[PDB]
Image 1 (tube, one colour):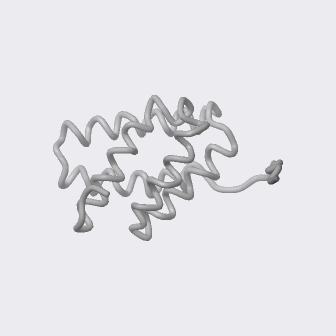
Image 2 (tube, one colour; image 1 turned 60 degrees about the vertical axis):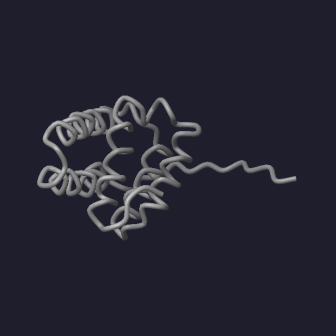
Image 3 (cartoon, rainbow, N blue to C red; image 1 turned 135 degrees about the vertical axis):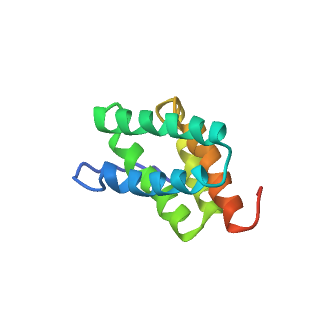
Length: 118
């Protein structure tokens, strides 16, 4: 068998910690990607933050995000999508309403690096 059974209820990660990067990317795109495409993403960000700060996001929905972020930082886009996928599995709706934006960001940020498309 396996029987997962895992829980964690502690203070960790910060909105400005998951946004710092997510935001650092935008600016990058802002000066690369179309103003429309970038505008779209940004718009999504505003939500992410709102939903994040607001508290509409789950604790395990943040700890998971940071992951994708941490990766995007190391350029581990492959990972970003990975974690992003895991989130799209359960917390698909949660991430939704903005996720779409990130989904794009990743690709974008990735492209910037050099390679594009998985």
